[PDB]
Image 1: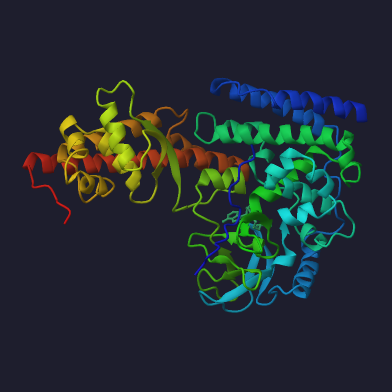
Image 2 (image 1 turned 180 degrees about the horizontal axis):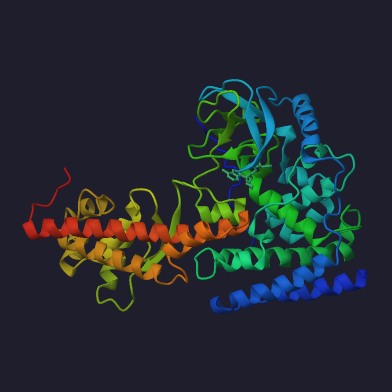
Length: 15
Length: 483
Ligand SMILES: Nc1ncnc2c1ncn2[C@@H]1O[C@H](CSCC[C@H](N)C(=O)O)[C@@H](O)[C@H]1O
């Protein structure tokens, strides 16, 4: 169902 | 003192802008940076803005604000649990798949709201803010925290004041991670954060496009550590309103849910412009409401979410492998890999749950171990493409000999990796049993133990597979054929 799943605390690049 | 802090931040910027020192000097560098940061921090007054009430005194305001703006506020209550901290607790029975939480877009803090706030002028000029939405959210949080009548005050006043990200660890708590895969990322996090603090401290105290910021009166290292830790432990990617792109966001009320194993049940509803969460499992009244954060490893949970998750069914470690340019068969192996859509060298994963290696890594190791005649069969003729197609499939080996070779290699490589740790599995277990430790120290020790337990599981699995395929080769059993 989820076209746009939401990941709590999704990992991002900080540099 | 203003001139004194500015000079300490100048030195910190220079130190944390220096190139990588080499893996063997990264611990030394980390301690040096910690020394500078702690000297600055002890000369400052902590968080610039603190609140008079307790954390739980502000949850009624969060609920009223969320309610007035269309969010779900019935069926749960906020409870301070020992293991996870504050979280949501069901006050009625909630059935699996029931839509029980929703949060309209107007409540969110987004990159878009950061731009249109008092941060806007500096955002429009600073190349780093424009490129790094996570850093933009952190300053959005700090600017609204320092603004007496912020729309988001009910959210900011219910956020934690401290986190268990490694930025908060003591030196000796991080020292437990020496010789692991994870510690490099702890070093990077610390250096990145200190560099960013020093850079923006200078920008805010001198640049005119930051003249109107609420942070000019006070912007402490503790402020910045708090802000980036708030974002890293709870930020989310959501679609833009027109659904064409994605953006980062903080999602109030729903982000109070703690993590358990399962599947993602939270999605964005573009048509109605709100985040929606359905119940991951049945929750009876009095049970904590959990969500599944995502398929992250315990390394990622410790470093970026500030917790270690026992029985994480998605835990993994890295293993770097590549075909050597000195291989007489390099050209053929690289061509087979390219046709299979696999690079000639890559960082793969070893998994705790069965199976320990992915289809991609299995395919890589099969090619890595192929003979010249096997390689030719995957390159030439009307069955070559069919042979490529099964390379990731455990049920269809290239040959029994190929399997014995590749599991022998993996057993030996995982065993070698285990020998590069400064403690053993048995020693780590003794530490956890026979020492009394802080939450943070236990996070570090369990993380290094977990890395080794995954390697040890891979050794045992590879040994079972090796013996299975050795017997097939001894019996010269007919190979399976894909039909
Ligand atoms: N299963 C779990 N075990 C321990 N801590 C957890 C957890 N799931 C979530 N957390 C904690 O919750 C944070 C994510 S935000 C979730 C709400 C948070 N407990 C709060 O008091 O505001 C993480 O950074 C971690 O501190």
